[PDB]
Image (cartoon, rainbow, N blue to C red):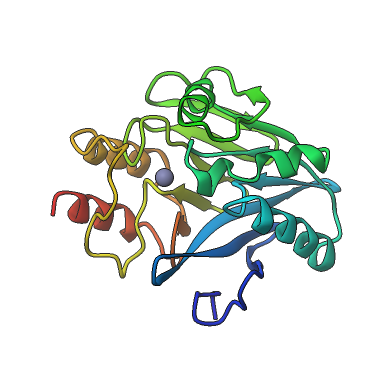
């Protein structure tokens, strides 16, 4: 019952409750003949929300904010983008228009600028070296090293053991690497091992695209990226 491209109506964004104070958000775009979905996270803190990733573009991000107000009814006050691609920063300007304080690592801001993408307003310090971790409200933000992209971050919600892997982690049904234009295929297995070692109690692992699973998605990703 996790939302998919087969059931989300065109142009809509859906939320899915994962645990106490934690939702995923799911949005779609059609590229060529194929409809794709992308996941992010929403985490409650006191009477506000922290958003992890845009909903992949400005139009979807406007829909996301409306869906959040309808279903949750608390303000999004901060966001984190987990890497520089459109599915993560596309819609940052919508978030800024809506009064959200937008964050990512310094490297992501640089890569987003270089790519001509939207750029979060604020940098997360102390994330520059592989293995760096910072607390940010109700989550930990971890830079595990280069994988899908040079800058990719993961986000853990310690109270409920939810790991948002972003595009560093593949869904179970995905058996080929697909697009690796910004990837570091050599470092990806080591990066996965760092995630495994850091979050051994995670109960839910959310990939950047596709269905949630558990810690088995980590080794699955290594297997696919070698393949
Ligand atoms: Zn990407």
Q: Where is residue 199 in the image (x, y as percent from the top left)?
A: 43, 44
Q: Position of residue 149 (x, y in %)?
A: 36, 36
Name the outermost residue toward the front: 32
Relative to the observer, which residue lies in front, 185 or 29? 29
Relative to 69, is 207 on the left or the right? left
Query: Which quadrant holds the N terminus?
Result: bottom right
Query: Which quadrant holds the C terminus?
Result: bottom left
The residue sitting at 66% across, 24% down in the picture is: 122
Q: Give the image quarter of residue 26.
A: bottom right
Relative to the observer, which residue lies in front, 59 or 170? 59
Name the outermost residue toward the left: 227
The residue sitting at 29% across, 38% down in the picture is: 183
Relative to the observer, which residue lies in front, 149 or 97? 97
Q: Give the image quarter of residue 141.
A: top right
Q: Position of residue 85 (x, y in %)?
A: 47, 41
Q: Give the image quarter of residue 80.
A: top right
The residue sitting at 56% across, 27% down in the picture is: 134
Vertical order, 149 against 52 (above or below): above
Vertical order, 164 against 7 (above or below): above
Relative to 134, is 170 on the left or the right? left
Relative to 112, is 222 on the left or the right? left
Ligand number 1: quarter of image? top left
């Amino acid at each position: 019952e996790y939302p998919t491209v087969d059931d989300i109506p065109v142009g809509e964004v859906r939320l899915y409750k994962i645990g106490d104070g934690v939702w995923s958000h799911i949005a779609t775009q059609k590229l060529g003949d194929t409809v794709y979905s992308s996941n992010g996270l929403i985490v409650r803190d006191a009477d506000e929300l922290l958003l992890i990733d845009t909903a992949w573009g400005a139009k979807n991000t406007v829909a996301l904010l409306a869906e959040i107000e309808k279903q949750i009814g608390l303000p999004v006050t901060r966001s984190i983008s987990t890497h520089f691609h459109d599915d993560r920063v596309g819609g940052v300007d919508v978030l800024r228009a809506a009064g959200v304080a937008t964050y990512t690592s310094p490297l992501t801001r640089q890569l987003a600028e270089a790519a001509g993408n939207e750029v979060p307003a604020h940098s997360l310090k102390a994330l520059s070296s592989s293995g760096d971790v910072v607390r940010f409200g109700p989550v930990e933000v971890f830079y595990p090293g280069a994988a899908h992209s040079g800058d990719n971050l993961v986000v853990y919600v310690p109270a409920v053991r939810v790991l948002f892997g972003g595009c560093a982690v593949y869904e179970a049904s995905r058996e080929s690497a697909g697009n690796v234009a910004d990837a570091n295929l050599a470092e990806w297995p080591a990066t996965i091992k760092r995630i495994q070692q850091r979050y051994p109690e995670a109960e839910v692992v959310i990939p950047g695209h596709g269905l949630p699973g558990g810690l088995e998605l980590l080794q699955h990703t290594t297997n696919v990226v070698k393949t």
